[PDB]
Image (cartoon, rainbow, N blue to C red):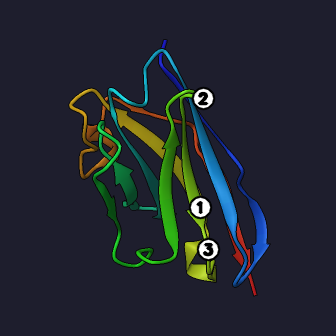
């Protein structure tokens, strides 16, 4: 019955910002590893960012470090991705993921749960 629901996607101009949301049901964000992945091409779903159960340890894909910020509101049971300095190559469906281990696994399908995704499209 676990649901992860992405929102906040959209069409944005290069250099713009978006904040994605992942509202979790049937699990607590403070007991799971929570993360973001993106399907950047047909054969590739890449890691974007993670935050571990304790809410202190974060990891970023090298290509988004310094542009994207992962956050979480435990009371609202919501995961966020602040996306700054957006560029065309960020265009993808973004997916949130959760793992009972307390830390996100490198590959979506090694995580317990993933959502249906939200489209982020970055134009010129």
Residue 42 percent across, percent down from the top left: 47, 62
Please state the horizontal and vertical placement of residue 96, each as a whole percent of the image.
48, 43
Q: Nearer the viewer, residue 118 or 22?
A: 22
Q: Are marks 1 and 3 in contact (CB under 8 Å)?
A: yes
Which residue is at the far bottom?
Answer: 124
Picture residue at 38% right of the left edge, 35% below the top: 98
Q: Nearer the viewer, mark 2 or mark 3?
A: 2
In this view, the residue farthest toward the top is 1
According to the picture, the residue beneath numbered tag 1 turns out to be: 82
- Residue tagged by mark 2? 76
- In front here: 5 or 70? 70
Identify the element where label 3 is drawn.
loop
- Residue depicted at x 77% and y 72%: 12
Counting other residues with Cα less than 10 Å from the Cα at mark 3, is it few (<14), some (14-19), or many (20 or more)? some
Gap between marks 1 and 3 measured at Cα: 6 Å
The relative height of residue 68 versus residue 102 in the rendered view (above or below) is below
Q: Residues within 10 Å of mark 2 (few under 14, many from 20)?
A: few
**Looking at the rendering, which quadrant does residue 23 occupy?**
top right
């Amino acid at each position: 019955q676990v649901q992860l629901q992405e929102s906040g996607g959209g069409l944005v101009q290069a250099g713009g910002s978006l904040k994605l949301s992942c509202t979790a049901s049937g699990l607590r964000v403070d007991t799971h590893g929570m993360g973001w992945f993106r399907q950047i091409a047909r054969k590739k779903r890449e890691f974007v960012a993670s935050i571990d159960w304790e809410g202190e340890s974060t990891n970023y894909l090298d290509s988004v470090k310094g542009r994207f910020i992962i956050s979480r509101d435990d009371a609202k049971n919501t995961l966020y991705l602040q996306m700054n300095s957006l560029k065309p190559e960020d265009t993808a469906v973004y997916y949130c993921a959760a793992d009972r281990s307390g830390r996100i696994r490198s590959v979506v399908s090694n995580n317990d749960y993933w959502g249906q995704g939200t489209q982020v499209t970055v134009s010129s």
